[PDB]
Amino acid sequence: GARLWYVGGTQY
Amino acid sequence: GARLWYVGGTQY
Amino acid sequence: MFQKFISKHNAPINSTQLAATKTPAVAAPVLSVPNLSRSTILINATTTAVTTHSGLCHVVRIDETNPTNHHALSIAGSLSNVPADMIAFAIRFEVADGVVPTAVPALYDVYPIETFNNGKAISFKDAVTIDSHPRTVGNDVYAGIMLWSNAWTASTISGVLSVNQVNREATVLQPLK
Amino acid sequence: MFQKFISKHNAPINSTQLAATKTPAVAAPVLSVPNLSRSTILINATTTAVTTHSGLCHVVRIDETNPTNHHALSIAGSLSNVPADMIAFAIRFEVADGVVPTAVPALYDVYPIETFNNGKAISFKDAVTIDSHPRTVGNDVYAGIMLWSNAWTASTISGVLSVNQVNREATVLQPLK
Amino acid sequence: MFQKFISKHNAPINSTQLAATKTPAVAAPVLSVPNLSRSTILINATTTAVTTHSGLCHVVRIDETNPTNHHALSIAGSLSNVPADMIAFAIRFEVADGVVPTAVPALYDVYPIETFNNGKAISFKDAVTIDSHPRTVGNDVYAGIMLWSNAWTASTISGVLSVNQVNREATVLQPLK
Amino acid sequence: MFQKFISKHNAPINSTQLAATKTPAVAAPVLSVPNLSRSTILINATTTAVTTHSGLCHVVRIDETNPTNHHALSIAGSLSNVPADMIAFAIRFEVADGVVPTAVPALYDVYPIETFNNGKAISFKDAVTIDSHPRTVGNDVYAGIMLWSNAWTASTISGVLSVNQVNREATVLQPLK
Amino acid sequence: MFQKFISKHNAPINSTQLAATKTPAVAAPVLSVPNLSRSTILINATTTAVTTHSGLCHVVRIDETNPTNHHALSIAGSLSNVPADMIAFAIRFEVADGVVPTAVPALYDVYPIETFNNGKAISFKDAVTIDSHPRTVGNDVYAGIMLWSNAWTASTISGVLSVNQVNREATVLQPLK
Amino acid sequence: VPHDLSHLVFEAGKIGRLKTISWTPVVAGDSFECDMVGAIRLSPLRRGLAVDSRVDIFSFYIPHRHIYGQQWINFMKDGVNASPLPPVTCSSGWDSAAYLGTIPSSTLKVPKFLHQGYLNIYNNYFKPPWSDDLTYANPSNMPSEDYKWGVRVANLKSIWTAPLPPDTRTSENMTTGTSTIDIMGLQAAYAKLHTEQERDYFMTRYRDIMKEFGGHTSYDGDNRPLLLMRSEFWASGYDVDGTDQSSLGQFSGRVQQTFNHKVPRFYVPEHGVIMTLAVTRFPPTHEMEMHYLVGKENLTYTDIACDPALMANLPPREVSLKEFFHSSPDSAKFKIAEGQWYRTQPDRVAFPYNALDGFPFYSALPSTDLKDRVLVNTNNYDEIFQSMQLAHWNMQTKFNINVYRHMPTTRDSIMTS
Amino acid sequence: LTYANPSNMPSEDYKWGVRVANLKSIWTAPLPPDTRTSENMTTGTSTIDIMGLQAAYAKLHTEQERDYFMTRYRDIMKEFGGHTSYDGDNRPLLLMRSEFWASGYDVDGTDQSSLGQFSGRVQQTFNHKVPRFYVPEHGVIMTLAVTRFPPTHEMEMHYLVGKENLTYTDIACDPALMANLPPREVSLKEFFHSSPDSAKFKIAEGQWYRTQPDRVAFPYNALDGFPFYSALPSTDLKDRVLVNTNNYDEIFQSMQLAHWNMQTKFNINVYRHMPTTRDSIMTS
């Protein structure tokens, strides 16, 4: 579904 | 592509 | 390193304490009352001195019921104050059926193994393949360990003895399975 | 030649130095405070002389939690100034639960192995398959090595002793893998 | 633990009691009349003292009929009042065909094994691969165990001895099959 | 019979002759300057008599570079004029990094094996699985054989000693491949 | 039980009787004239007493022709009236090429094994993996068994010795094939 | 003309660490294409296969200018007599540049663009985003294992493995008057916090705060290595059945995975290196993780009802490794989004397992510390393999590259002519 | 190889045969060692002959060609647009040539100790066909085999990464430059991680940009079973080109069948004008 994890950008 | 190795002839 | 999960003698899980003198002649007496397929005794054995090449035993009574004639009989002892002449060969004999031995008849078979004796102590762990059915109709068959030497002096030889009859396997826990 | 990567006794990676006298009676005391699944002690053991066929121990406390009733208990010693009567049979006993032994009760099981003693030194490396669950509800189960002989004199017997409870395997590096 | 179902010496199921003195010289006599492929004797051997490095035997007579030249000959003894010099190497020799030895000729082959002797007792269990056909047409081939030492004194050395010629296997009951 | 192509101790192909007295105290000295993964010394060792249960060593310096923490360390000796108390347990210790021992610190681990001593000679061949990485950052790790007994008298004990660190296998020629 | 069809020492099928005194110094002489890949001698060895930790040998001459550098060299002895100090380590040395040794140079390699000595008798059966090619161009390479101890007295030590160089296997008859 | 710069690669590394497997120096104006095809193997594991590992292969382009800055610019301008470009220094170990998939030259030094190049690729795409940059100067400055097997990459998103940014505000004060508040000031207060919150959660990167403006920033605006191609896959294999007396009923999982990666032709604007790195990881399955609702004792209306109004309107919730792991300290905290426990589900491993080596799971407890307990804890996989001198995983690939240039030629260079 | 008799050739040269050349790499096919890196034209003290210079270049050209490509008569001929019979230079005539890659499969160990261990089994079916051929004169037809592995060393480094300070000439790949300066003399040291600064060889400028070495992680260089070059090159040109066989001894288990063995059925068919079996034994 919708986004979940938020680190402050993109983490591979 | 083009030749590379040059020994002074043919080496098997 | 990997763990060795194979042994020559897989003693019953339980041991029966012995304590009882004996007179180890040729007609080698019986240490502890014979169990059924496995036991392990630690009978501070007391042994009247005997200079005549005879001896005292400890065997079990083999289970006579399997369509497989030949079974594996594994023994294993460690004894002290053992005359530094101790040889533990194994044995088998058939008494009449239903009868309880008090010592081996004149009629028994021997099977050598790997017994090592130092001075006052002896041990072993080997396997002998004996025939499981009564050689004669009306009798039963018994087998175990026998201590044999020249000079059997006034001494209490303590240690332990185990005998089993591979009727079944005892499989334990293997961590990678 | 290829390297043998299988052993009978895979001692813990670490050893705890012992040093403590003892009085090795029948009610065989306990050498070092029992650890949990493996230890290896090298307790220049000091041993008050005792002429009565009793003895002193060193076992660990087995881990009572695995749906597999039967586990493998491997021991291994090398001792000096050991009376040339030394027999190292193994053992197991269940004390009440949560209780810490200071010696084996009158109630314990024995399992023979392959102990070899010369004069003043003895070693071993064998495997015995014992039952891992408390035989009775409210207690725990302990197991290890026991030194047993006739005459236990005034001497400090140094050497080492290791006991493990194959709960898990310790697999090392194999160069062809 | 799993049961070891492999052995180095699988003695015949039956043993023949011996009792007969001997004079163990170089031209090493023969203990018991040679059987055919396996026997196991427990001849309280009586041995005239002999200080000259000679000795007395016990071998069987190999079966000379199999398109396979090389066979396996496994022996196994345990003896008492054995001079603490006892070496049991094995042997093989070919006498003329149909002839029954009463001792080994000057012509025999040796094959070392793993004999261990303490003081007054010795045992062994090993395997030697000898050649099964008569090296020469008109003769037969015999092989077994030989006791060899310096000083052979006035003593009756009892114990047992077994020799077999892996012609066939003896397969017993395996509980997981 | 087929040839056994598996061994417990695969000594380096080369041996370094030793000859150098030593004083075998607890702070057990070092026989020969430590090599790197395997050596085999035959140092008619000369040994100042010492009655205090201490001893002298011979180990190598383990190679600290393999993503596999646990390695196999196999030893093997045969010594003469060895006090009939000789126990060869193995060992491991970590000295600071780059430092060359001249004897074992107070801090070392032991691992029992199968040492057999008669009177004046002792041998062994076993395998112990030790942990290969420096237990602490700034140091290195060493391991080998240690001779330990009560009474160390005025005598030159010659024999040999080998220690290897199964980092790699040494595979020889197998005739059926 | 099934028959073990694997051995550590598969002696040649034939043995050469020895009889010849020797003087076992450091520059350890040679017992019997070196054969080629296997022999087995039973040289009632006569041994001038020598108190200096030197010794006498028996090796064969390795076959220098196989693209496989590392070969397996298996030995096996049983000796009497052997000083109860006997250590049989193995060995290898390269003499100039085509030359026949009469004893080992100052330059030889050692490889420990599993030698057991009691009092007056010693045996062994082990395997050592040596390098098969001449370490230097113009020479050949020899290897075998060496008896080493402190005190070598006036005595004839009889027994036997076998050495082989697994160049090829000797496969016998297996009854289930 | 096509320049075949193909070569074989024999690789190996740890589990959650980024490692360079290949690099090809490129010149300004050449086109680069590669076809990397091989097989990925894991060290032999102690039991049968249970869970597939996922593999990520990356190819990036980092121009030199990005690395030497103005120094490079001058170098190109100066031309033939430009001052040589100083390489970087390394640590005493043949395996001291490993992370750079190259053997440190004889003097234990290596290209800075290999080092910084690598540094730049991690600090921009792998390092957690609230986290601090790897400002390592030389490989002789990075931890032994960081440069042996490579720096630790981040665990696969879980609930506890992707906490809210630790610097995340759980409250915000507006200094008010003693007996009055400015209704208009309050409004403003909210506008500022918004801009702050966004930076905290999503725009920790310039290039990111830009994008939300509806603009774009060239990888040249923020000197970021350009991600050219990305392949991801799950490696598998088969079990091997033991068949001797003792190991009959025992198995060993063999992970053989054929993979392929294709970097489409690419136009190299300027001179630089193309780095190709690999990263092997397992899903963050811990043997002791508990469902938040089941680990936090008294359940309030807010925790159990999932009231939209509530979840959609209160501050992030600060929780401890203790409401998620069965023994874990009450003290190791992290900020979670309210109702996060209802958007997810942990994996569940029966206790019978936590005593078993051969399972690619997390045995040990987390790492009290945020960072460390996110970027994967490799070592907790050491017990899963048998023997290993080929690390945790090894790879054998044939890097089929093809570069189209305007090169001299082999005979015209050696032909003084 | 001006060996007179086989009793004159090295033991292993005549046991297993003389060493063939490694498969072309950068370091495994250096420029001819006698390759000129400069050429002087003796000039006057305060003048040069503009026309003499021109000529100087023409001669060096002819020299350079012989050095690099026409070390063989038959070769200096071909570049003249002519041809030379294998009878002009007494060269054995190459009738047929087959090349292939041998493979096999792994064998999975399954006992307690070697469960997770494998042994590669290389079984390769091959075939070779020598088309019918007309034998002009009496002679022998020799059929030889040569098995080789790509020259993968466990310690070869990328030239640019092994040579410390990078100049404009090394890193820019300026066409004008590469296309116009002398061959570059390098050492086993700009290519191998420990190798002596002293073992040199001549490479073509920008050669490092026309190629790429294979790369083997350090974790390997401590592992026997991999058909790679462990050891360091051989300081000497020759030796370090013609393959160093011995560095493969560690890759196999046991071997009394060398490194490789072959079982082939040579199906030959010769058409003659022969007597016959009965007409020769028939005095008649």
Image (cartoon, coloured by chain):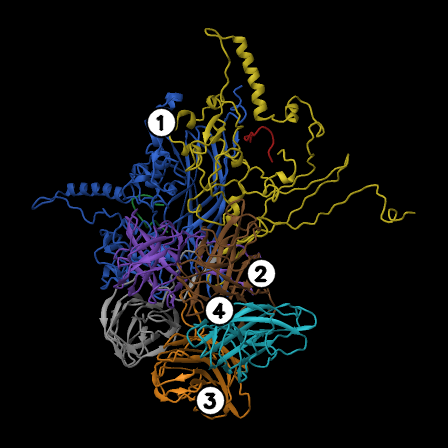
Chain colours: A green, B red, C orange, E cyan, F purple, G brown, H blue, I yellow
Q: Chain of mark 2?
A: G
- State the residue position of label 3: C104
Where's residue G167, x and y in %?
A: 57, 56
For the residues tagged 2 and 3, is the chain the same? no
The numbered mark at residue E114 is: 4
The numbered mark at residue H72 is: 1
In the displayed structure, C94 sits above or below F19; it is: below
Structural distance between the alpha carbons of marks 3 and 4: 31 Å
Judging depth in this view, the residue of H206 and F39 nearest the camera is F39
Q: Nearer the viewer, mark 3 or mark 4?
A: 4
Q: Chain of mark 1?
A: H
In the displayed structure, H231 sits above or below F53; it is: above
Q: Nearer the viewer, mark 3 or mark 1?
A: 3
Judging depth in this view, the residue of I53 and H189 nearest the camera is I53
Q: Are marks 3 and 1 in contact (CB under 8 Å)?
A: no
Structural distance between the alpha carbons of marks 2 and 4: 21 Å
- State the residue position of label 2: G169
> Label 4's element?
loop
> At label 2, which amino acid type do we have?
Glu
Residue F44: which quarter of the image?
bottom left
